[PDB]
Length: 284
Ligand SMILES: [Zn+2]
Ligand SMILES: [Zn+2]
Ligand SMILES: [Zn+2]
Ligand SMILES: [Zn+2]
Ligand SMILES: [Zn+2]
Ligand SMILES: [Zn+2]
Ligand SMILES: [Zn+2]
Ligand SMILES: [Zn+2]
Image (cartoon, rainbow, N blue to C red):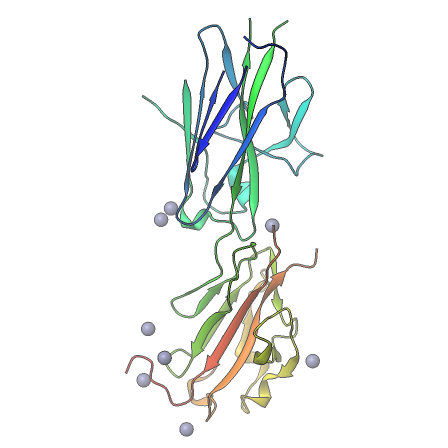
C-alpha cells in the first residue's frame, strides 16, 4: 500500500495491500517565487524504504534519458529514465542537490535564481517500500522546473530564455550616449537572431524575433562598421554591440534582435526591442 499527498511544493509518500500496484504518481512545479520543494517518505516499522534514484542527494531521474547510464527502476517492471545530476539536467553552473533533513526521511531541494534553466525541465524522484521474495509499493514524484524569464540586467546585458513562460513580451532596452552597449546572451540553448546580426537587424515593426525581416544596420546608423559587434569566439551564442559614443544617430531609431531556440522545453523565442535614443542623457 502506497499513498502520495501534495500541497503546494511539498509531497509526502506514506506506506498490507490487497494486491500489488503501480507507483502512486503526482507532480509539483518549481519556479520564481516557489523555489523550494520538500519530499518525505514514511513507513510502518516492518518496511524498509529506499529512494529512486538510490542516492537522491546526488542524483535525480531524467525520464527523457532512456538510452543511458544507470536506469531508474520502479517495482520489477517500471522505469523513469536515467540518473542525472541536477546541475546537468538544469544545465547550470552551481552544484544543486536534494538535501536530507537532519534532526520517516525527508529531503529539501532549494533552487536559487541562478539555478533556473533556460528551458523548461522535469525530473523524477520516488520512494519504494519493500515488505519482508518481498513485495514493493512506490510513489513517483515528477518535479517540473519552469525556465527563468528572459531579462535585462545592468549595463544592458540581456539573458534570453526559451521556456513556455519565459517570453510574455519583448525585452525592451534603451541605448543612448551613456548606455552605448548591448550584450545578448543566448546560452547554449539558443542562437542569435538574425544569423547576420553583425551587419543586419530585424525590422522592429513585427515586435517578434520569430518574424524577422532583415535590414542593414548602416540604414539607421550611417557610421556603422561590422567591428561594432564582437562575438564571444569560443561562444558564438553571446555578442556585444558597442556604438561609439559620437556615432549615435541624430534621430531615435529602433531595431530588433534576439535569440531563437537552437536549430536542433524550448517553445518560445527571446525578442529584444532596442530603442536608440538620440540626444538623451539617461542619468542627467
Ligand atoms: Zn545562490
Ligand atoms: Zn546568491
Ligand atoms: Zn539544453
Ligand atoms: Zn543580408
Ligand atoms: Zn545631434
Ligand atoms: Zn550625459
Ligand atoms: Zn534613458
Ligand atoms: Zn544607470
